[PDB]
Amino acid sequence: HMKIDILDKGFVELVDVMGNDLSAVRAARVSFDKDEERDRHLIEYLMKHGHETPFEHIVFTFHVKAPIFVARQWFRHRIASYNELSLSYEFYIPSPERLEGYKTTIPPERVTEKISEIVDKAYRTYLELIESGVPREVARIVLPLNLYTRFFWTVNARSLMNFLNLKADSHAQWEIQQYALAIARIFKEKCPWTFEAFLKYAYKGDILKEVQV
Amino acid sequence: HMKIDILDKGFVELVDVMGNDLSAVRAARVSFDKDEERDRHLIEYLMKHGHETPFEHIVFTFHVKAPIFVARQWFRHRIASYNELSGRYSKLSYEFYIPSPERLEGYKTTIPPERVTEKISEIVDKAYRTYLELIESGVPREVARIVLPLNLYTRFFWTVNARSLMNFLNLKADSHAQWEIQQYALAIARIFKEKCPWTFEAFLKYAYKGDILKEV
Amino acid sequence: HHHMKIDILDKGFVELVDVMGNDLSAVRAARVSFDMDEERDRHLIEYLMKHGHETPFEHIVFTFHVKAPIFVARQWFRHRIASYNELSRYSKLSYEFYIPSPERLEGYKTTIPPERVTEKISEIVDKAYRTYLELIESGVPREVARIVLPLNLYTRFFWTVNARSLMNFLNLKADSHAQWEIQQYALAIARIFKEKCPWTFEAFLKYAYKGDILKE
Amino acid sequence: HMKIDILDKGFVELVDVMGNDLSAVRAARVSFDEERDRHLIEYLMKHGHETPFEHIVFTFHVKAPIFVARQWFRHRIASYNELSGRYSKLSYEFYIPSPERLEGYKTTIPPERVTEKISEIVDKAYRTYLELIESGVPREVARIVLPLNLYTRFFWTVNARSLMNFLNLKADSHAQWEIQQYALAIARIFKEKCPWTFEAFLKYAYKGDILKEVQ
Ligand SMILES: Cc1cc2nc3c(=O)[nH]c(=O)nc-3n(C[C@H](O)[C@H](O)[C@H](O)COP(=O)(O)OP(=O)(O)OC[C@H]3O[C@@H](n4cnc5c(N)ncnc54)[C@H](O)[C@@H]3O)c2cc1C
Ligand SMILES: Cc1cc2nc3c(=O)[nH]c(=O)nc-3n(C[C@H](O)[C@H](O)[C@H](O)COP(=O)(O)OP(=O)(O)OC[C@H]3O[C@@H](n4cnc5c(N)ncnc54)[C@H](O)[C@@H]3O)c2cc1C
């Protein structure tokens, strides 16, 4: 059902989800059983007064493809579960549009060309080492930080909201902002009430109030 | 739609589950995209080599009604999520765990087992009544209720991934735990086996550290 | 040499057993370096606190020894990003209980005089204890007997907590909406944290602290 | 500060430590004779009562290739502060495996060629990086061309229980040789600060292989 492309070869794909906004309502009340307006008011109430633990009973699993340098920033979120690929070889090459804004001394397209060339040289050294009998765990160290990896991320909505706080923000690196908007979108579609209360009361960042879904 | 009664008025109820044995398999392979023997071999392989992180992608929510002493041993499992009943969003009720006389069997007591049951009962009744008398007096509940005993039943939601569930089972599905938390762990075990049989079967065979799940 | 003890309630306490690092520990983590002028290091602590960059404060760690009634302990133990070891089989067990003083019931217009409330609590507590002792005398195992004991029975535990998690604790428990009893314990924890990490603590009150009682 | 050099440019260094074997013994006893206290450590470890070891805490300063750092940061029950790829100044150094690293494989070019080929490619990527910086390209973008052998630095605060889990998984022959080396350095510092706990860990709860044959 839900897969969003990010960057040149990335994605965020939704694998599974447990619960919805009413999961947090039931957990707060500690009752397994509905009144829309009242249950909506509770979500807002929880979020307004920082009673956030009921949001932990909503869990998501994502399959994410992102460059290693993005993954490293992501994996710093410790309240979450991860399984990473331990195979195929693709790389994020920034478009020229990624480098307009910045005043530079060579054309933005030349930057894209240069990055692409160095990637090609590195990969080729790697394949050459692999063909020589060099084990992969050694041969791969020449590969650049823009090598795509993939991982499964299982994460509850509370910790997901910490992630949005930190990464759906103009101080975060643009690349990771893009992934974060994809995660915000899937989150909004599954837990609309919780996302809305979040934006309203607890969200510390800037982009999700700018840019729809 | 799965509930097990525990002790005289307790229960463990399955509220929700995300995934099944195949969720760990997809995690280990990092593939969203069938061969059944193949998939089991992998579950067994993961278990026996201690690669437990794929099992974190299976998750349960349980609703447990337990006496406070039990809940305190339970809440010590930090890698999980909890919400306890508070009289702030929901109705509170007052029930207490009274051991059956069978519970003292094995122990050579000076007092008959039924008399132990009755003494526990008497104390519950007297504490509960002192409590009520205090509320009626205008003592706030937060103060009044400090006289209630440890066998007062509480309720909570517990959301826990399989890896941490297995840890719980290693520690509480064991003869070394208090008998009351064992019965709760047996119920956990049973719900877990129902929803992830391949995993549970591999857990017993390879990773389970306790004793009682291999007799019941 | 690190060591402080603050008495809380009638028989409770919070004791500092050890501390790793100081304000400069956070400064060093944030820079990934070995610094020890104060002007700049202080600016940086504020900077970090302001912008919600809290990870460096995780590199300051405290160990506490806490004697608190079980009801206070249950709330405390909900803080999962911390390490706990509660008293057991390695030490002698003692039996003391939190009796509130009449003044605790001030402002509450009560049907019986506050001294009577205090006296009622002692009675029912004493009764529960004496029943406990008689069950123990009769051969009832302690894990069964003890379930009659009330929520004001004092326990002891060690708590090892880092400064970021400590600050979260103070945000939740040093607040007029927490139960008074725990507010008192939070005030002792705030006191010890101020003493040992003055810059962080002061930055915390100005930029991040969410409660009301510490700013009095 | 104890400091142990690992690989060509790396290290583990001890920034601070809280407590020692007795910190666990005090935690276990819940209270503020050497044979009795050593014997308690053994007992705890033997019967699975590991929570008292959470009250011994370390902070390390580690300089490691990014590929080692990445395997390391999967240990979530710890606190980490790293140089910023976007902002921090770096030493731009790189791990060049010795030729001896390849001995044990049959390869079709000599191990020294392999070492040299790794150097060349590292060299071209670094120079390309410098031309991009030189050109006005911000570092958060220009750095994506650097290889995974680039050395980074991080602070690591971790309690002894979590540290023992790390040693179970990294001071082990199935782990990549490079992280083994770092694990041995961490095992050395641990052993020095907490001799009783360390001996007990080897004897009752250590699941790896190498710390039992490598002092
Ligand atoms: C106004 C108010 C009313 C409340 N009412 C109730 C109630 O009725 N019942 C009830 O049970 N609790 C209630 N709580 C919550 C209860 O107080 C918490 O269990 C306690 O405050 C622990 O706080 P914590 O989870 O932040 O601390 P810790 O558990 O130490 O967590 C520290 C921080 O780490 C993060 N964290 C740690 N583990 C996880 C995880 N698994 N998933 C996501 N994030 C994680 C969170 O960001 C958290 O803030 C209420 C809280 C407030 C503020
Ligand atoms: C024989 C025996 C006797 C015991 N006696 C006592 C006693 O007297 N007093 C007492 O308080 N406890 C005692 N315990 C331990 C107590 O039972 C545990 O707190 C409880 O069983 C929870 O286990 P856990 O920490 O593994 O689970 P969780 O809290 O869910 O942690 C799960 C796993 O994550 C890791 N972990 C989580 N948080 C941290 C952290 N902050 N630091 C390092 N690692 C972490 C651990 O590897 C742990 O195995 C005893 C246990 C045993 C087996």
Image: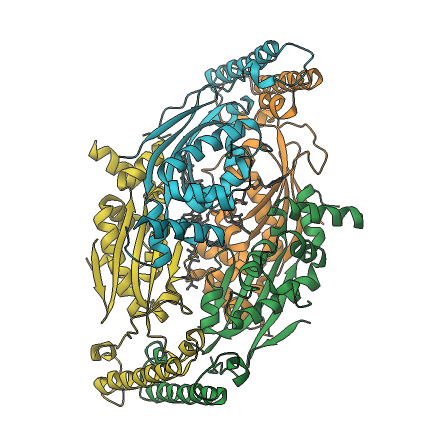
Chain colours: A green, B orange, C cyan, D yellow
Q: Whole-percent x and y of residue B202?
A: 50, 59
Q: Whole-percent x and y of residue B134?
A: 66, 17
Q: Whole-percent x and y of residue B137?
A: 69, 15
Image point 37% across, 27% down: which residue? Answer: C5
Image point 45% across, 67% down: which residue? Answer: A72
Q: Is residue D118 left or right of residue A17?
A: left
Residues B21 and C97: in front is C97
Q: Whole-percent x and y of residue B42?
A: 50, 68
Q: Quadrant of ligand 2?
A: top left
Q: Quadrant of residue B3?
A: top right
> Is residue B20 shown above or below A43?
below
Residues A67 and B106: in front is A67
Residues A128 and D213: in front is A128
Q: What is the quadrant of the C terminus of chain B in the image?
A: top right
Res B195 seen here: yes
Q: Quadrant of residue D49?
A: top left
> Is residue D152 shown above or below A50?
below
Q: Is residue D114 left or right of residue D169?
A: left
Res D158 seen here: no
Residues D37 and B47: in front is D37
